[PDB]
Image (cartoon, rainbow, N blue to C red; front, side, top):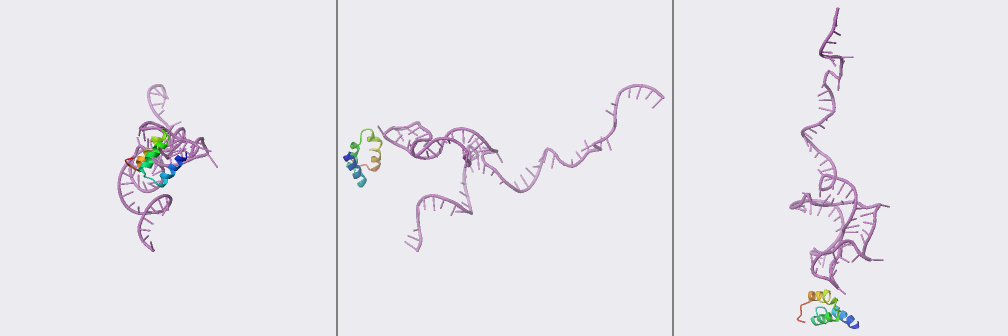
Length: 49
RNA sequence: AGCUUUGCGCAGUGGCAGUAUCGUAGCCAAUGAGGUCUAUCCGAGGCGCGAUUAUUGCUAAUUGAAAACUUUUCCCAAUA
């Protein structure tokens, strides 16, 4: 959970981070990995990661 | 100090639509209305009833009128 809080702080302070977003996909549980974790992410950026 | 964004009225000009606009002391609703897409996603009014030339006024023609018609004791047949 603390990892999730730190990831939320990191994304808020540093958006458009390809590696951070890619890793935040796999912090989130499987039900929420697609509908919210990767859609708005692809909206944010298109990094190779 | 100019410019500029949003909301709100007040006007002015112009365009489009008339199978639609409006009403709610009726009910329900961000404590979730409503869900065919894509649903660990979408997020706002809906439902019922009522009004109507499918918003409502005036303006001006026309028609219907209205004003009138003798708006007053006739006929077939009987007798003197």
